[PDB]
Every structure is written in structure tokens, then in C-alpha cells.
Image (cartoon, rainbow, N blue to C red; front, side, top):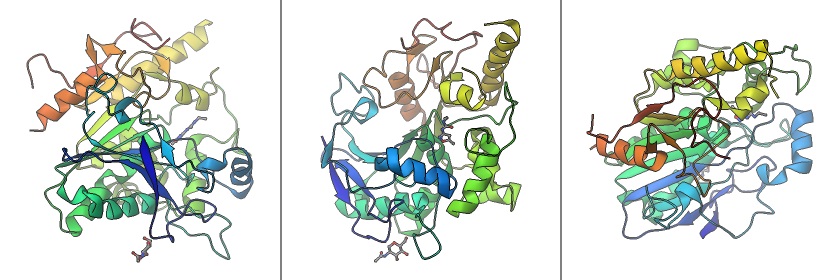
Length: 351
Ligand SMILES: *[C@@H]1O[C@H](CO)[C@@H](O)[C@H](O)[C@H]1NC(C)=O
Ligand SMILES: CCNC(=O)Nc1cc(C)on1
């Protein structure tokens, strides 16, 4: 199990002002640290945040959090379940800011909710340094779905934070799972008048203003003010990053299809095949990646994450090969993208 620690700096809060926190399982024999960002969509105005507070309150508040959690998948400490990093120090950071880990605003007389995702990550890092992170050799910032996009938005800020705090020897890297979305043409279209109809670009643009959202500096400098929503899209923000980042993405991701208004005749067949091709195209110059041709969503904290293979190579193996490459390798590849054109043309896709 991983044990809960609420942040000692209680000014860093979840949406409703309760303290944020993290779950920790230490491994005294290891200098590797894994910090995982939970996902779970987001909200972007008073009305849809109020609805989230009624039926998704654990994603907006810590008052009902349990004292422990079980680590699964890449967060498992058993080698049977986690061939990659089973002996690492394990941290799970709950997502209670509803801001895709981008926010920097407090609850106040003018703000019904606090949006402090970017500050939550920084405060977790700061408090961990006194519990052994000061002696780390690698810090891997991982995450799934909204947490995967959160890795892309924050990995270089963690690197800069540790440099400025005086720990230049810690190597910071990122693992972004199921957070590589396309602002593509949708299969059916509606103008942005409420939550359901509002396309991701328009929703994120409004969210950034509501959250006081922040993006990586080099990406901000490219797109400039008013256009920071561009930096929430993986293929646009990744070229601006300096830390090594490994990208995991199903070619036919279920959340991508949902925001494309897809739930088979010729028109839809062509649409789905073109989505797969566009995704593959955006990964062509990503040297560390794992992209199977499946209809699914998320992978790395599922207990059977070791089952899927691309070209005969599992994800735990590809991550191990990535580790080796950061010390091309004979029979130990790091770029693994399916080329077949339809969901589950890879026989190892999840059932
Ligand atoms: C608590 O966190 C806030 C937000 O980052 C920061 O402004 C403040 O200095 C912190 N307080 C302490 C005592 O570290
Ligand atoms: C309903 C589909 N889910 C999402 O769009 N989830 C997301 C999107 C981003 C960005 O972070 N989580």
C-alpha cells in the first residue's frame, strides 16, 4: 500500500479549499522515484464545476480520501505485475484541481473554487526532498489521460525547480499516457453553447482564463497571449520540451473518439482510418513512443498492462530499453508504432 500525506503547506489546496496531498511508498534500497498524476477530465465554468462537485467530489476535495491506496500496474511493487520499476519509490498524486494540472489560482472572495494543479505538483516535489528525494538519481513524472497531458505541461517546470533548489544531479523525465490529443476535424459538429457541444479547443481556451492556467515557457513564447490553448495538444507542445519524454497513446483512443462525436458505413470507416493515420503521423519524430492499434483508453496503472505488444515488444520492455538508451540497441527498441489501419488489427489489444 501507499500511505496518504496531506500537504504541510495548507495554502496549496484542492478545488474546495481542503489540503491537497500525495500517497507514498518508500523503497530505501532505491534511488529511482516515480511520481504519477491521476486523470479524470476537467471543468471550465461555475455551472459544470458545480455539477462535478456533486457527483465527482473526490476529484475536487480531500475530505473523503482514504488513508491508503494499493499500487497497481507501473505503481506495483511486485515484479510479477511490474517488470519495469518494481523496486522504485512510488508516489500517487490525486487529481483534485479539475484544471488538467495547469492552474495557479486560490479560492477567494472572487473565486468560488481554487485551481492549483501546477502548484500542487511543485509542492509535492518540495516536501518529498526531505523524505529521500534529495538523494534521487532519476525522477520519472508519469500520468494518465488528463494526467498524461499534465506531464507534458509540467515536466520541464519540475526540472527547472530542482535546478534552482540546488539538485542538478537528479535526472527528470516524463511518461505521458493517453494524453496526446488531436484538434482534428470532428465527425459531427456543434457550436460551443454548453459543456456537451463545446469543442476541446474552445473549452480549454475558456478553462485557461477560469483557472489562471499556465503552460511551458517556450511553448507560450511561440503561440503568445490568447493562444496558449495550443500548448495543451501534445504534438504542438512536445517539440518545445527539453526533458526526455516517452509517449504512450492508443491510435484509436476512446476519449479522442468521444470528443470527435463518434460512438460501420463508408463515411465513418474513412473517418476512423484517417484518425489512425494522423496519430501515426504526429508520432513519426517522437523517438520514444508506444502506440498500438486499439480502441481503448489509459494503460499504465492497469494490473494487466504487461499484456499488449507492438511488433512483439511489451510496454514494460520498451520502457526498460528507454532507460538503457539514456545511459540504438540490438533487439531492445524504443519507437513502437503500429501501421495496421483498424481497431484491434493488433491481436494483443485489451479485451
Ligand atoms: C505555500 O505555498 C504557496 C504557493 O506555492 C507559497 O506561495 C508559499 O510561500 C508556501 N509557504 C511556505 C511556508 O512554503
Ligand atoms: C470526455 C472525454 N474526456 C476528455 O476529453 N478528457 C480529457 C481531456 C484532456 C485534455 O484531459 N482529460
